[PDB]
Length: 99
Length: 99
Length: 148
Length: 98
Image (cartoon, rainbow over all chains, first blue to last red; front, side, top):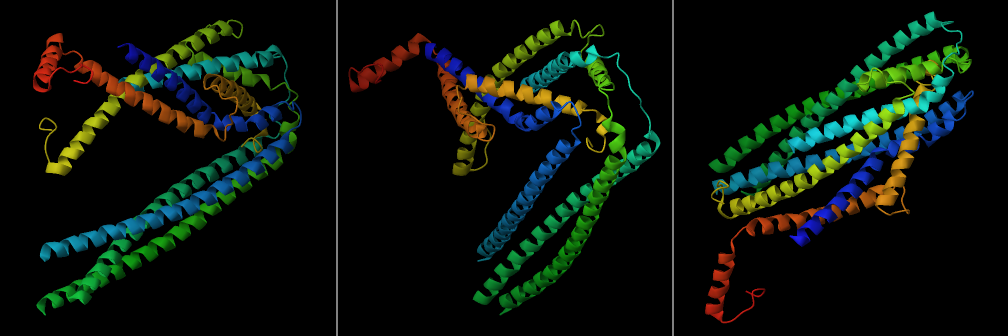
């Protein structure tokens, strides 16, 4: 029982640490707002900085788009090969039945 | 798991309320000079009409994106059935040549 | 001889199915390309409209004069007022509400972690139960958990 | 929308700055709890999965512990009887080795 309460305390430590790390994972985008925080500090004409941030975001989004497209192609390739194996197994199994 | 789902919902709501209160605290300074005022609605007519047209365009874009995604889907299943037919035909052809 | 004839007929039918599915896939790919072009046209139009609105309003919104800045504070205060069940919520007394709601939030997180611990142990116990079930099924085949 | 609707009036900018400050606070809090001054948003995922493995180890441990405690409900008599049976079969043995 003593070891078990100790293990429960250790599990609580792990839980809190993991929850904190997850929370920062969620706030991942917020760290990108460092530009937004710096931009907001302009307190004056700041449309050019907005446009620069928008261009950077466009570049990032295009990179992510290409990454997603190529990954989708790879996943589709894997899916066709899996389906081909499925059909081949069906045919071989049916022949084994018949033989 | 049901209980934990409810608890997570409650935690999310509490976090949102705390963030709203933090927002009030931050914008207390902006409230400080609430007496200030300025001109408004100078070019609102054309701006409002263009905003309406842009909203229409955005809605059409959302429809287009949804149709694009779904069509990608049906094309995917068509390719999968095509690959399944390919595998079946190849296996049966191999087996006929063997016989 | 008869067996090979049957398999040849099977292959003919499979070839017909392959032709049909190839035609269907070609039509689907053509439609997919058409919808890609249509979508890209829609984002092009949306971006053009956004840029044109930006250009038109350039002069309008530059001279904000930090005077229409405080309505944002008004909307934030009101949004908290409905979100936080505190109609008396004032930017003056909103700090006590801030600290109290933060205390509630941290209490909720602690209770959430407490529930999470027991949830994880229970789910893993069910996982071992399931593993026993799969081992039994593979060794013997279908059977209920009670018989396990 | 912010550039097109510059009448937005930096409200979204204010919210994003507040979110940035909150993220800074959260990152500091994690660096404290996890005791990882060496940490970045880009590589925090690696420590997250590492401590996920850590938490899985702890939970699996405590799961075996829960089963052992639950079966510990067995009364004192069963342990004695099993111990004496093992003794009579093999000869005198320790309870730990029994």
